[PDB]
Length: 285
Ligand SMILES: [Mg+2]
Figure 1 (spheres, protein in one colour):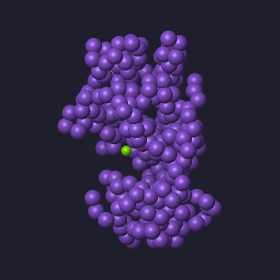
Figure 2: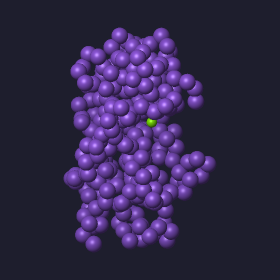
Figure 3: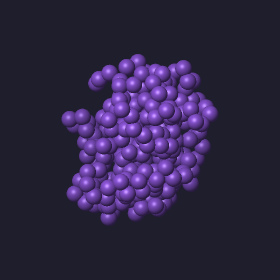
Figure 4: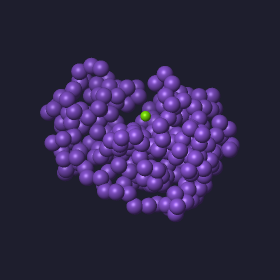
């Protein structure tokens, strides 16, 4: 139920860093946890700067240092679960470390070398991908979402910017947003992509299904933005020539983003069947 994605050449190592909101707390050459030699920063996020480093213990390995969200037994089990995720469509978690210069500590994860799907969209004149390519990217990441779901776990923050296209693959990079199905407390989704029921009922496979539909919509068509947030709903075929030509695609997007979670696709496999069917229709005509 997957297709062939174009090969995306990774960036050379001498082109991975940006030029440094506040100044970074670490700079090139700094040694973290006596294992990681800092190379620089690759982005500034809500948790502060996100660093790139050499892992000295593993030959050739480049890692990402990202701030962690600041009862040891429970925290130990959650860290071991992240570390043991085996699926190649998900970024690897290598370590969880502290540092006297960064109070919150770092999660140490695999550096995925490639553009995000948002980056690919921004390189187009219409700011969107061709519909067959966007569907192919979603089909490619569905095994990774399902791997989590079948282990009682959800990704919560799927959006074009945390799916990275590398080589002929895509990887999910947002390990920090993962929670158990039905987890209590505040869930770190993104408004405009997150399902409406999460803030009151907790996350579920159905709320992940919702973010997949919003992500696919964002990859393929312009979406109205209100106050920095993608407005709710799917554009109408009356307003979108893409949807008027592919009415089954419009229907799929509405079902995946149904206000009532019970009306959405029940799991990733049900979504894949219809999604691959929409693609074959588009490629047939
Ligand atoms: Mg996130």
